Image (cartoon, rainbow, N blue to C red):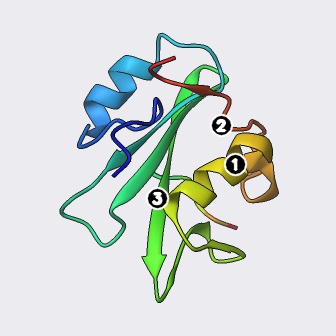
Amino acid sequence: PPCYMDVI
Amino acid sequence: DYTAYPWFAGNMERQQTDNLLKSHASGTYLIRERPAEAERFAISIKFNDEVKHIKVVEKDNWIHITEAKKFDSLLELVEYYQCHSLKESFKQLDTTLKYPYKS
């Protein structure tokens, strides 16, 4: 669900 | 100038990119420009029935998809992830940049 991959 | 590279899609937007990659094999990818934005490229990749998108950031002298691994150029960054799985920075995305979309 975020538009772009979330960076941990 | 990346127009020669088979993975370079130019100014393609999200809808076009999704519509294009969704029919391709897992590992198919492209880099696209985002002229308006502070992150002027994105990597888009088919992976396990979805098309995923990753922001490419330019900050100070370097370019990166994560601040933990910084490159001097977009080409170097792309060539790194051609051979090193994205999973080192995104678990849930264990693939290399395996097939350029024009191939």
Identify the residue position indicated by label 2 in the image: B97
**At x 61% / y 59%, what residue is drawn?**
B76
Pair 1/3: label in front:
1
Q: CA distance from mark 1 to mark 3?
A: 14 Å
Single out the residue that lies furthest toward the top. Answer: B23
- Tell me the SS state at disc 3: strand
Q: First in sequence: mark 1 or mark 2?
A: 1
Pair 2/3: label in front:
2
Residue B55: image tag? 3
- Tell me the SS state at disc 1: helix
B42 vs B71, left or right, is: left
Single out the residue that lies furthest toward the left. Answer: B36
Using the rendered image of the protein, determine whether residue A3 is visible from the camera's viewpoint. no
Q: First in sequence: mark 2 or mark 3?
A: 3
Q: CA distance from mark 2 to mark 3?
A: 15 Å
Q: CA distance from mark 1 to mark 2?
A: 6 Å
Identify the residue position indicated by label 1 in the image: B81
* Label 3 Cα neighbours within 10 Å, binned few <14 / some 14-19 / many ≥20: many
In the figure, B25 relative to B64: above or below?
above
Chain of the residue displaying label 2:
B
Image marks 1 and 2: residues in contact by CB distance under 8 Å: yes
